[PDB]
Amino acid sequence: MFENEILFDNGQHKFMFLGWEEKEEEIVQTNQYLILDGNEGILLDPGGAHVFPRVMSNVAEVVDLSSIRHIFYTHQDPDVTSGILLWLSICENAKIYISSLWVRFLPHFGIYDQKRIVPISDKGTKIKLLSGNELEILPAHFLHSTGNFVLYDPVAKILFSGDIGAAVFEKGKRYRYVDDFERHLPLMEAFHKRYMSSNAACKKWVDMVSKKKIDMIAPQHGAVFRGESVKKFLEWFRNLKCGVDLIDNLYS
Amino acid sequence: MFENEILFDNGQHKFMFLGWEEKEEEIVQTNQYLILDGNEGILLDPGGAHVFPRVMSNVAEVVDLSSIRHIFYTHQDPDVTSGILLWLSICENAKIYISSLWVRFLPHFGIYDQKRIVPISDKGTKIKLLSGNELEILPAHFLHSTGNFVLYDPVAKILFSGDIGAAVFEKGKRYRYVDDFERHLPLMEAFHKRYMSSNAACKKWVDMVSKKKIDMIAPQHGAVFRGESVKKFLEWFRNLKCGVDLIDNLYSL
Ligand SMILES: [Zn+2]
Ligand SMILES: [Zn+2]
Ligand SMILES: [Zn+2]
Ligand SMILES: [Zn+2]
């Protein structure tokens, strides 16, 4: 498997889980997403330079690249942003949304028209689509990056969670969707305990995002949460001891 | 005139503050450092792709590029790592040291020989140099990056502090050294309160590095701390409320 897959479709609006490399390579596994709304496209963490040819081809078989009007970057990491020059070049109509904390860091990649970058203030923002639909950019700071956002699609009822919900797959055992949360949890525990900053940051985020109607959680790594695994993930994450909570394993 | 400057020199060992661009651009300002020990060089956060030509020429005017044996990356951010492919190609004998948290993230920049990367475990490590001198890689996690290190040079008594100690200069008002700490603090406060993760991490880090003899703190952004400003910085940082301490101000009520 691992072709482009449709997470949500109501005719006017689609949320797509883009395809994967067919064979495991020596690189951290990543997920990219495409939202289509009328005639305009939105890319979610379309990713690094090395995967760019593959992701670009996944996108191009679904939509003309000139119809990508918005590109959302959750944070600054290489698995998210390092293809930025390539995306700016091939998607001539795309605006890029990233935390204000990182807008002056992206020019380190190379030269581009910096007016195509929209800073996101800490408390979040909304992307206004031409059809009148909206995408909500919600704060998710320190999970893990100090400047970090998630994106909630209120039409699809899908939360794109970035690094939150990541899973590290066992060799040869990748899978796209979470059914049994308890058998999935072993793939998530180490990543979250080490990368996420503290229970205070996790609890704050869960309290905020739980106000939304979330049918699926789509992370930037690992497998997409469906069904009851959504609420079970939010419950587990809210109580997680992580990061500086466990500081005695990180210092001295 | 922001040319290469020597922070420490004892003949056998030098610690250099590489030069700056003459014209300011719309980009976060960065510092690069070069350690020379005998005939081998160590680069500290040599930086992104856009600044690579300038940093490379600053290094090449001081030492052979084939003498760079070690390149240290404090963390993953683009102002630190996005020149990795260029540095790997022009410093053919260099190994790259970075947190194990990022070792599998770096291949997203592009293809390179992954045997050239040395993972740094969370507790840190030492670079053993051919002379018998050492450089100490010390943990600095969550200040700001979750996988983040500083480097202490016990010969020079210089702490390369990464993003810790960063200052955001007012445009056209760059300067290389901290004289008056209380007059430098306005350039540092916003960055530290927002990017650094919590006082718990800051206090742990200050307690740890304060056991070392630190004459100068050299940050990856801003100005180098000398004299009493080093001590004032450490005490200020140890008590700083930052990051998730202020998380209720980063979310709407
Ligand atoms: Zn990340
Ligand atoms: Zn990621
Ligand atoms: Zn940084
Ligand atoms: Zn930096």
Image (cartoon, coloured by chain):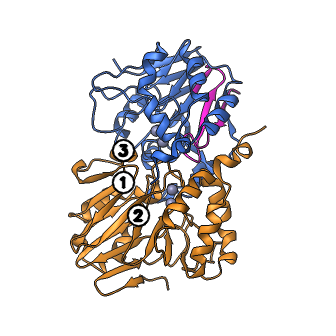
Chain colours: A blue, B orange
Instruction: Check disc 2 and give the amino acid type.
Output: Asp
Q: Which residue is mark 2?
A: B45
Cα distance in 3D space between marks 3 and 2: 18 Å
**Between B247 and A54, which is closer to the camera in this rendering?**
B247
- In the figure, A164 relative to A120: above or below? above
Label 1 C-beta lies within 8 Å of the nearest ligand 3 atom: no
- The numbered dot on residue B247 is none
Tell me what residue is drawn at x 30 percent, y 63 percent.
B127
Q: Is residue B154 visible?
A: yes
Tell me what residue is drawn at x 70 percent, y 45 percent.
B250
Mark before the other along the chain sequence, 3 or 2: 2
Mark before the other along the chain sequence, 3 or 1: 1
Tell me what residue is drawn at x 37 percent, y 59 percent.
B83
Q: Which residues are magenta?
A: A132-159
- For residue B200: magenta? no
Label 2 C-beta lies within 8 Å of the nearest ligand 4 atom: yes
Count of picture labels? 3
Q: Which residue is mark 3?
A: B108
Q: Which residue is mark 1?
A: B98
User: Dot 3, crowdedness within 10 Å: few (<14), some or many (≥20)?
Assistant: many
